[PDB]
Image (cartoon, coloured by chain):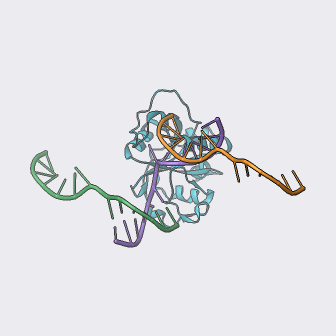
Chain colours: A cyan, B orange, C purple, D green
Amino acid sequence: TSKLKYVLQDARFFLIKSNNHENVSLAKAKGVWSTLPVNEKKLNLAFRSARSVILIFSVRESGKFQGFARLSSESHHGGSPIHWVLPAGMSAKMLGGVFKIDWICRRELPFTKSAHLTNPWNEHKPVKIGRDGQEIELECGTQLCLLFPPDESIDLYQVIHKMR
DNA sequence: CAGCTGAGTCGAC
DNA sequence: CAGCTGAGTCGAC
DNA sequence: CAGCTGAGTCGAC
């Protein structure tokens, strides 16, 4: 995992929570993500200050993580629309900011396999606990990403090249 | 974003 | 007007 | 396939 550990060096980690499976599947297919404006501003500021910003995805009530990815841009408004399945009470403009993301792993990891990992930045609660945008301490987030099964469909050349 | 809440005075120093 | 924020899991019942 | 069943809330954290 030396290439994987390289991508994770000095990274900041954020839990991303989706209300539906459809938007995570579209995120994996198109390499983009959108979030509410508060978390959008948080991720934009993290992108500018951190070597890498890693998003760890978990569909609400699914009992698993669905993979993780690296932010490759700040959010962009006004591009070609992403046709998200809009959660209840949310409009398309609320998710108007579109981040480009490079997926590092698109495989699943059940919460049962992460039960030994606690986040010291969230009162040492298990890493499965949190709302959208919950930040995860460096070492806890690194170990979590290393728990995912290997994704043979991922080529880390491009993400590593744009980090040089 | 978009719907929501709340918007002190008075006196010592 | 400025300030705030929702796309948490889990046990009890 | 194709006929069938079932579609928790609330509060601590």
**Residue A22 in picture, x, y percent from top left:** 37, 43
For the question of whether residue A125 can be seen, the reply is yes
Total labels: the figure holds 0
Check the picture and name the quadrant holding the N terminus of chain A: bottom right
**Residue A79 in picture, x, y percent from top left:** 50, 27
For the question of whether residue A164 can be seen, the reply is no
Residue drawn at (53%, 58%) of the image: A144
Please identify the quarter of the rendering in which residue A76 is found: top right
Q: Nearer the viewer, residue A122 or A156?
A: A122
Residue drawn at (48%, 44%) of the image: A154
**Residue A25 in picture, x, y percent from top left:** 40, 42
**Residue A64 in picture, x, y percent from top left:** 42, 56
In this rendering, the answer to whether D5 lies above or below A83 is below
Q: Is residue A83 toward the left or the right of residue C5 in the image?
A: left
In this rendering, the answer to whether A161 lies above or below A15 is above
Check the picture and name the quadrant holding the C terminus of chain A: top right
